[PDB]
Amino acid sequence: GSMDPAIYFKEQFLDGDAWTNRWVESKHKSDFGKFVLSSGKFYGDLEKDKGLQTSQDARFYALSAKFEPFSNKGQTLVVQFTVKHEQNIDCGGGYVKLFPSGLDQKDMHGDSEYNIMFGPDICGPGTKKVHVIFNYKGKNVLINKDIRSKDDEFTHLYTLIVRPDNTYEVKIDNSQVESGSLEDDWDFPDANIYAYDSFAVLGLDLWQVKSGTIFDNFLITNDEAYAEEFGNETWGVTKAAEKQMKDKQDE
Ligand SMILES: [Ca+2]
């Protein structure tokens, strides 16, 4: 329809283990850790809150999902997903990578030829940051701003908005935490820094010591307002009932 958002990618893991038809395990290493479909020990809803959980301690993870390729030139790009560190994590990634066409999904590991890297990373109390990394001039450029990530056991929504006028916005739990211009907050005037020829693959390319992190409700769209709606329909419905079930079990 004329007022529909473009939904480039969406994944909520609502249909059992049919997700294995959409996500590709990388074969680069023989001993990657295994992702598992799980809702956890405590949850908002048993079926709705099923996501990909890291099932093994002290392992690299390499899983990716492809979608119909698109370019963000001339329009907004929004990347959204939920991260739940149910384990009370010591050290481990919770970020995504957005790759252009031509990625060997079976060869993905520590891949640097992505367009954008985004999301929480935790490694001891001294590392508790949200990455926002852009590929430009063959260099992966990190944000000059310090964004603090969530460190508890609960589900949190992470949102990156990239606009065609070289502006960005970061939200945690549907609330702005950081905002500005791409020329100012990175070490890159070029009107097309924001723009990439193809997005084709979203990758989970991580190391964790204490595993048990759940990933859910992935959204790549061109609509800010829809991401916010979807965030509330998704993370916003999870939050209260999850806290409630956890509070219960704590006795
Ligand atoms: Ca789900």
Image (tube, grey):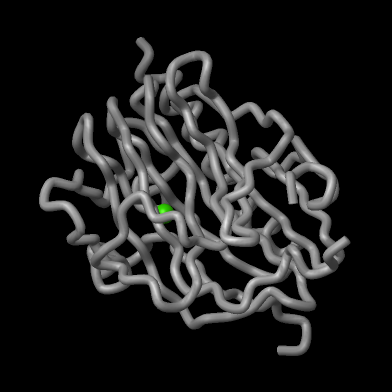
Left or right: 110 as drawn, with respect to 135: left
For the view shown, which residue lies furthest in the bottom direction?
Answer: 1
Q: Give percent across and percent down for residue 1.
A: 71, 89
Q: Which quarter is ligand 1 in?
A: bottom left
Which residue is depicted at the point 54% across and 24% down?
Answer: 128
Quadrant in which residue 2 is drawn: bottom right
Which residue is depicted at the point 64% across and 61% down?
Answer: 137
Q: In this view, does 52 lie above or below 130?
A: below
Which residue is depicted at the point 32% across and 37% down?
Answer: 207
Quadrant in which residue 41 is drawn: top left
Quadrant in which residue 85 is drawn: top left
Q: Give percent across and percent down for residue 208.
A: 31, 33
For the view shown, which residue lies furthest in the left direction?
Answer: 30
**Residue closer to the observer: 62 or 191:** 191
Which residue is depicted at the point 23% across and 63% down?
Answer: 17
Q: Is residue 130 above or below residue 91?
A: below
Left or right: 250 as drawn, with respect to 7: left
**The C terminus - image quarter:** top left
For the view shown, which residue lies furthest in the top direction?
Answer: 251
Q: Give percent across and percent down for residue 54.
A: 28, 41
Report the label total.
Answer: 0
